[PDB]
Image (tube, rainbow, N blue to C red):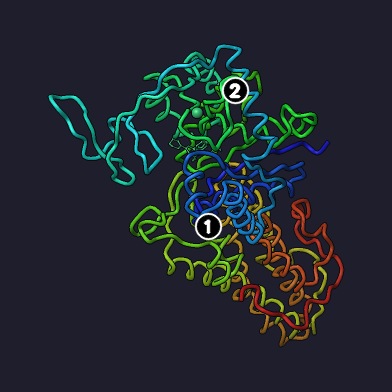
Amino acid sequence: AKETFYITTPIYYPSGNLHIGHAYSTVAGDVIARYKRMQGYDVRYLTGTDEHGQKIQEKAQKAGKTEIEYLDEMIAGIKQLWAKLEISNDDFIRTTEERHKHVVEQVFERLLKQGDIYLGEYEGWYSVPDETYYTESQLVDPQYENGKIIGGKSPDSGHEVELVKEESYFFNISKYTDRLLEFYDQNPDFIQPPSRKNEMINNFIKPGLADLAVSRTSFNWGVHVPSNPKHVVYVWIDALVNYISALGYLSDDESLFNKYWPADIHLMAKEIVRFHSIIWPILLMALDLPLPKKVFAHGWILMKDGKMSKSKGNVVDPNILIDRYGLDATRYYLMRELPFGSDGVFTPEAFVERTNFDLANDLGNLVNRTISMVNKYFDGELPAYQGPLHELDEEMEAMALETVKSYTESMESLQFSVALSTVWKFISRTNKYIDETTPWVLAKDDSQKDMLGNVMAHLVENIRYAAVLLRPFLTHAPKEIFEQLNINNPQFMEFSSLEQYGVLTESIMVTGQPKPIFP
Ligand SMILES: Clc1ccc(Nc2nc(NCc3nc4ccccc4[nH]3)nc(N3CCOCC3)n2)c(Cl)c1
Ligand SMILES: [Mg+2]
């Protein structure tokens, strides 16, 4: 077998308007997926949607549609974005799918039988419009009476909160506390970034874990608890098991599950990392199922006003960006501007600057300079590579291998903006190499055609290296670079083709008519 690799994005909630940060997750998952497939893994890459709850019932009803009708339309639009981003997801899990709903049912009923889930009462500070409960310390403008909390406001919307008591099934999770802590100890790389682990052991595990209310009686649109249909499965169990339902767990064909579980990486935004680090492995322990090998939270893409939403007036539509500026530009900015363990920022100015200077100038003009010259000096015939003939070739070819080495180390540690900048260090140095070798000077001396060709050989081989490294990130530039150069063998486009510098042992006819990589 190709060794398997299973990567996931969270399931998105179909409110209707998607930012660059929802886009960030799918694009990054895609970079990981494309990269793993290039390394020879049997990849499965999952995304999908969280389709249940009170808020969808309401959305549907305002739009004047049934839930499904409303849902199908939100999802058509979601899947359209991911097609337009060229997300290489192998499947798309909808929580409204029988395959998912059947898992939810069975999972719930089993934890009931085991005695992990019990009937009690939830009490909390509820916000009607937010469809969300808040802790006393999360309240804004709290109201006190003789030292006791009596009311306050939602920190999201600022609507008044109201104390609600309600009947809930509860999943007893603190019973798995010491196992979880042992699982963290035996799996040190589990939580990425790892600085995220202690804040969580501190803030959430050691206080320690409260029983989790996992159903409600207050909505209809959702998976009903079979032994008790008045109760509907709340977000925790419904959303998490997306990752195992998509694989045919507990169906009649569990081959995908047997093949791909456990996941190698759950990728997520930081707001739900706690849920995937604590609740999720505990639920898996309760099901006697293997735990995922890694969970990775990325930061947010912020503005100058500051975090991104419909409300502040700071929403950026990935869609218009692809249209305005091109696909490769958009994918590039997102991956290039979000460091591991940090938030990033969208400025229209920063965007155009990164697209112009990195992509169009550094890369695009290296390619056009190089073809122009092969066409001026050799009428389109690129002399086959020979060896490191020029004083600078030996350390430049070393730099090419060092580029690939340092890129791979960044790709494995999830440090994408660093893998990209490393490639661009090599990009720039290849541009420097034209200035250094001044081919036009060589071109005037007939006894220098060998060296001229050596210089050209290097430039192209340097371009080819950068195109291969960029393939997980950019779905257009690399292919269009290989065509322009008339590198037409699929093998010369793979990672293995980078182990030894100078791979074009025969003459090739670069394009007569080179156009911009980035228009
Ligand atoms: Cl893969 C994945 C994706 C998301 C999440 N978390 C997550 N999602 C959502 N979505 C909206 C939402 N509301 C829902 C109601 C019923 C069923 C599914 C519902 N989904 N809402 C929350 N809330 C946490 C507490 O405040 C209120 C909402 N948490 C998890 Cl744990 C896993
Ligand atoms: Mg009822």
The answer to which of 121 and 264 lies nearer the viewer is: 121
Q: CA distance from mark 1 to mark 2?
A: 38 Å
Up-down: is 321 above or below 339? below
Q: Residue 449 appears in which quarter of the rendering?
A: bottom right
Name the residue at 44% across, 19% down: 211
Residue at mark 2:
108
Name the residue at 74% across, 49% down: 38
Image-based side of 103 in relation to 259, left or right: left
User: Dot 2, crowdedness within 10 Å: few (<14), some or many (≥20)?
Assistant: many
Question: Which corner quadrant holds the N terminus?
Answer: top right
Image-based side of 431 in relation to 344, left or right: right
User: Dot 1, crowdedness within 10 Å: few (<14), some or many (≥20)?
Assistant: many
Name the residue at 72% across, 78% down: 371
Question: Which corner quadrant holds the C terminus?
Answer: bottom right
Q: Residue 455 appears in which quarter of the rendering?
A: bottom right
The count of marks equals 2
Most distant residue in the left direction: 146
Residue at mark 1:
334
Most distant residue in the right direction: 506
Q: Position of residue 64 (x, y in %)?
A: 52, 54
Disc 2, SS:
helix
Q: Position of residue 53 (x, y in %)?
A: 51, 38
Q: Amino acid at mark 2?
A: Phe
Up-down: is 309 above or below 295? below
Q: Amino acid at mark 1?
A: Leu
Image-based side of 304 in relation to 386, left or right: left
Most distant residue in the bottom direction: 444
The answer to which of 314 and 102 lies nearer the viewer is: 102
